[PDB]
Image: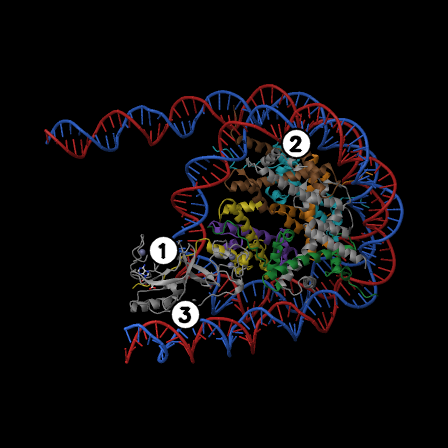
Chain colours: A yellow, B brown, E orange, F purple, H green, I cyan, J red, K blue
Amino acid sequence: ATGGVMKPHRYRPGTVALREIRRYQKSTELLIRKLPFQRLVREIAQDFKTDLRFQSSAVMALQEACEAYLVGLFEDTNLCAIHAKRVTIMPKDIQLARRIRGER
Amino acid sequence: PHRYRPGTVALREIRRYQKSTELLIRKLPFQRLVREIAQDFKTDLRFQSSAVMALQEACEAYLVGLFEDTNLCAIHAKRVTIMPKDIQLARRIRGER
Amino acid sequence: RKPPPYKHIKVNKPYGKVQIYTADISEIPKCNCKPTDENPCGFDSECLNRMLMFECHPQVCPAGEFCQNQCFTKRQYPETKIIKTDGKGWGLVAKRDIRKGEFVNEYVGELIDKEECMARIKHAHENDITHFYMLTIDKDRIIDAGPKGNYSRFMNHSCQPNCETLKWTVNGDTRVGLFAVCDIPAGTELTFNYNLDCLGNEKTVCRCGASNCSGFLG
Amino acid sequence: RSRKESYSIYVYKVLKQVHPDTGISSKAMGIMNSFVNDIFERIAGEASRLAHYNKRSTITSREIQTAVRLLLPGELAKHAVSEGTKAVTKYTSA
Amino acid sequence: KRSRKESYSIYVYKVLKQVHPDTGISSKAMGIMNSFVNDIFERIAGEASRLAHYNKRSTITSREIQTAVRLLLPGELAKHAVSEGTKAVTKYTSA
Amino acid sequence: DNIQGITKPAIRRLARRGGVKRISGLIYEETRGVLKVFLENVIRDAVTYTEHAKRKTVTAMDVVYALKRQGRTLYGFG
Amino acid sequence: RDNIQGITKPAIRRLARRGGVKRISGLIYEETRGVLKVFLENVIRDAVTYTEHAKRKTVTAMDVVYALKRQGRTLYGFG
Amino acid sequence: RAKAKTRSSRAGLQFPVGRVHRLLRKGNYAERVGAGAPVYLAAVLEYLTAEILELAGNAARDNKKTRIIPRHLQLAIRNDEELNKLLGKVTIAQGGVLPNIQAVLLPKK
Amino acid sequence: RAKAKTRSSRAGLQFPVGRVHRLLRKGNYAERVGAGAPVYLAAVLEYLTAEILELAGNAARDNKKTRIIPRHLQLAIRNDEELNKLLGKVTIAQGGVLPNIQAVLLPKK
DNA sequence: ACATGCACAGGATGTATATATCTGACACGTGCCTGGAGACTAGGGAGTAATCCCCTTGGCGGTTAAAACGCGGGGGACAGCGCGTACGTGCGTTTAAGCGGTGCTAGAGCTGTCTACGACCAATTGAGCGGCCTCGGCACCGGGATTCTCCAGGGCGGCCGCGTATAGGGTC
DNA sequence: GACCCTATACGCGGCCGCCCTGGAGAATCCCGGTGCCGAGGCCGCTCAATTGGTCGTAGACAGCTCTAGCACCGCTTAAACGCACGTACGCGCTGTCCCCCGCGTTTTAACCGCCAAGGGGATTACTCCCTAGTCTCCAGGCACGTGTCAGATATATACATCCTGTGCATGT
Ligand SMILES: Nc1ncnc2c1ncn2[C@@H]1O[C@H](C[C@@H](N)CC[C@H](N)C(=O)O)[C@@H](O)[C@H]1O
Ligand SMILES: [Zn+2]
Ligand SMILES: [Zn+2]
Ligand SMILES: [Zn+2]
């Protein structure tokens, strides 16, 4: 005389992660929100010249470039992690990737 | 019977070759290698001495930079030894093949 | 005598203001298995849909009809029958041996919301209903195999089970399938851990009979 | 309300020549414009350097050919050289 | 017969004697300095050249050279190079 | 604090498209720094171009030129 | 003519030492010979292209310098 | 005159030989431009465009689409070795990436 | 007429404004070269040369040598951050490397 | 005589597909007008020939540094295990992005005008380049002075075994 | 109730890990000669920079239009955020064993120096044809407009398997 729902086993850790990997490697959308990225862009630009204006295509181009940069960087840092016999990427992996690339 | 421990002559050599500014590959072997590589591009080529010297300088600089990146890769994997997979990781991240 | 009558349905039936999320055939995942493979999208192969609890689609899967990963829509339930249990009601026993990992069945019922679920539990308390078939598929969606369901609703809880519930995504929506966790020979009654049943009530005793039985449902 | 030159019509002509029943999106056409301009600039710049290295005032088909060999990788270079030399052979005899 | 090969050797040596009066320079180091000056000249000249083309100009001016300095040089190098070149231009036009 | 607008979910999505399964919790802040560097450089050069044309508005071509100047050619904006 | 074997193991060890490398696996020598041969082939290919464009039968130091520069490995000290 | 005949036609090309000639002249590459240089360059540009467009059309057909979109250009470029090498340092807006998961991240038995 | 006055002397430079002007004119950078462009560029080249040579002379002094050699240019370039950004992709013949050994390779105490 | 086992004509809705309607996305069609094309000329860049005369190639012989080879052994790579916590999965709330619509104005983008800057040319002349010579900075050598590494034996902190002191328990 | 049997931690060295120097080579520096060859300083000349003047057009400057960038507001709702939970992954520790380093001996081939020889790069002199420049003229390509034709797409009507309920055959 109790009732109460049953609960299926949650997905094993790493299954929704792989689902997301496939999903976001299938799509071409922009993965950052647009207003936050635009606010960050204007804030960064305030240091170089005040009262600047931006074309919408300027901010969209910036977002495309930055997102592509971060995706490629994450590919290289995942290679670093896997080299170190891991599957978790850590800040040291980003630092090794950027040092070998030439940025650091 | 006196004998240094395995890793002190290696550090000695590291210091000796990071202090020097000289070519570490022999001259005639590298020159023959360059000529045999160039045979498959055009036959009966000549080579100015400065040409082969510039090639050797560039190749040595390339390999030294590559070994630096390889050493960083090996240290990343918590090793001290460099292995072929380290060269491959360095070249993959650089952009080479 | 016989179990109380229920509309034996075959696919999930929505009810109330619940809403499914069925995607178009273009946006369902496609694996890399090939029709010439040893067992295309087979159980033991490296199917990228099977590994991720995705169900292949014959009109999307590159293996075409050689895809052994359509176990939900084709309903390859191994044959089974219903037997009254000791003090739990009616369980089910299959007709053959089952090797560990064989898709045993699919849980299916009526899709209800949270407030409708608590309404049904209240109505059950009003008439001291003791058999509850709820199973939360997600927030705002619960399966209720009470009125409508299949043979799977006749599997009992056991603290040391031989089957389990796993969520797959078929045609872009979640479905729950009972899988075999150990090599079950026939004659053995099938039972999976409900894995929770206590909402706010007295924790009905668990007469499962397992060695590590928790006594109650928890 | 002013003219804006583009490679769109020529890209579309080449498209109908190889995939007669396939279209192309406006965004993809823009990407093809950028691609043609990029490759044009690469080849023209490399040929311009080639003239200057040899102290010549003229960018000729010979230097465009050599600029193609430097910039294009392998089979692309071979087929581009063949195609261009066929175009120049056909042009000079007409 | 023997053609004249131009180089920045005498100017590099003149600049060296300003900043290190009692210091010489090897022929190989002077060759490296020649390559460095030619490389930097080509970078700035090309950047200002295409910077004029972007704006649909045909004249490479001190504004083009200045902007090519800011694009190519980092931080303090850019600041000091800009100030030095501005000084040389503003003192060139008063003579 | 607009760099905090590059939220954790956004960075996780960018990691997914890069094929990253597990992500250490120290990555996020680190990644923000990386982003804020890259952006800066590009925007710096973009504004430089914008100032040389005597415009108050940063044009998509300024961004494209900055990116190409940095060796990151971008197709699709001019 | 196995001329790539003239880039001997001790030479590779010296190049590794100047790179800071302390201990070296014995499989590094063939890998490094392959890497070196690939790099040399690219540079010599471009240098011979420059040479043939100038109608010359002699590869000059400037051809190598231009090839390196166009591959992004600018080399000071030869012109 | 004699019925102007559009040099691209004389070369058997689709790309504009005359416009390429004008861009070479007004672009400060050398003080003289040969006659066959624009023909050669237009032919090479047309060839490369045809190569990319063919691969992209194949990719767009693999998805059962009849329009080429940036995704298909990206797929064609990254899936072809030499086109990948030519356009390695290039970013295509709205392109995405190749689907690729490392073999160690896949669930094990 | 006036005797002569090289434009470098007018600008107060050691680098040749006239030769830089000719190189700008004969390099196909634009069809016109302003009066102040060679002056500005000669000043900038002179500044960069002076910066590198200052650091290289310091490096030569630190090695008890009174004559700059490629090693000292390399040391000056790699030890300075700005010159290292500028010349990050440049190889210097007979320059060698900085003396760097990673801290993990030093003998354990 | 009768209700158990179980069915068959009608309903009834999922199931499969024809069908009227949107919403763009391009698809031809004008309408211009600007920029290629034809035609012709002038002159300079490039091609060809001849000639010199560096500098690359090839040979020879000796010296000796360096590579090749062998071998012991030390330490690092690498496999295995355990644990504990950090990260992934999911839920319930909250926030802020995105969308749409409105409204205003900075400033991009263009035109018109005119001027003052840069190309161009001729004459002039001094700066910079090739050639040549010398003397000091550096490379090399050699012997002595530190300096650094390595390992063999002593003190210096253990816990550790063993005989031993202290007190509980059974018995007279 | 005291006395003797008996157990159990107490301390008393009892060897031990394990630093700590001390000294022996080995390597590296350091300093004085020594000589040699290249930096650097000068000379002569030539050719490129400077002076001057002319002329044309690039661009600066003003002015105008109207695009598109920004500011704001309200609603929807998806996404972000914070927390709970539980496992699987990172990381530390251990052992083992193999492979690479350090060093000695042998072998080989790089390197150095010297000498020819001839190939081919560099230079010069002509010359001739190919490109810029120009002027005229027309059509190719771009801007804008509207048709057409899809996919998509919600509407709607017939078909296929299931559901029904009282009646057909029957064992009581
Ligand atoms: N192990 C068990 N012991 C006792 N009762 C059980 C057990 N498992 C399930 N039940 C009862 O069965 C209900 C669960 C339902 N899925 C019914 C399953 C049951 N076999 C039936 O179909 O009737 C619960 O309300 C319990 O009262
Ligand atoms: Zn499959
Ligand atoms: Zn399948
Ligand atoms: Zn139990």
For label 1, the residue is C161
Q: Are marks 3 and 1 in contact (CB under 8 Å)?
A: no
- Residue that badge 2 annotates: I66
Q: Nearer the viewer, residue J53 or J100?
A: J53
Q: Position of residue J10 (x, y in %)?
A: 43, 80
Q: Quadrant of ligand 1?
A: bottom left
State which quadrant residue H25 falls in: bottom right
Callout 1, which amino acid? Pro
Q: Residues within 10 Å of mark 2 (few under 14, many from 20)?
A: some
Q: Secondary structure at mark 2?
A: loop
How far is disc 3 from disc 1 in space, using C-alphas?
31 Å
Amino acid type, callout 3: Tyr
Is the CB of the residue bearing disc 2 within 8 angstroms of ligand 2?
no
Q: Nearer the viewer, mark 3 or mark 1?
A: 1
Q: Secondary structure at mark 3?
A: loop
Please say if C15 is above or below J157.
below
Dot 3: chain letter:
C
